Amino acid sequence: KYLFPKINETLLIDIALGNRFNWLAKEQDFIGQYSEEYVIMDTVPINMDLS
Amino acid sequence: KYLFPKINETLLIDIALGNRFNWLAKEQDFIGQYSEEYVIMDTVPINMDLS
Image (cartoon, rainbow over all chains, first blue to last red):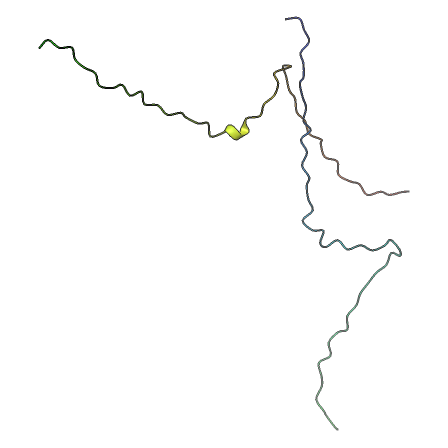
């Protein structure tokens, strides 16, 4: 009843925590900052009013 | 009315009983007294405003 107690082990519980997305992860190469895209809008055609 | 009564057999029926948790049986070495266990607390990344 006079000894300081003892610790026998620790185990370092760790979990790995995935992403659920990285098939979305494509890789640019760190140059430039502005990127953009664009579309053409629709044009409904018109009747032939020959007058 | 003068003969000793005859036993025929004694059976001793017996079956052993399992554990249903015997795959949890981890075996340590019986040293020390206490055992603690700990994880790392999280730390989210930060934006860096390099000004």
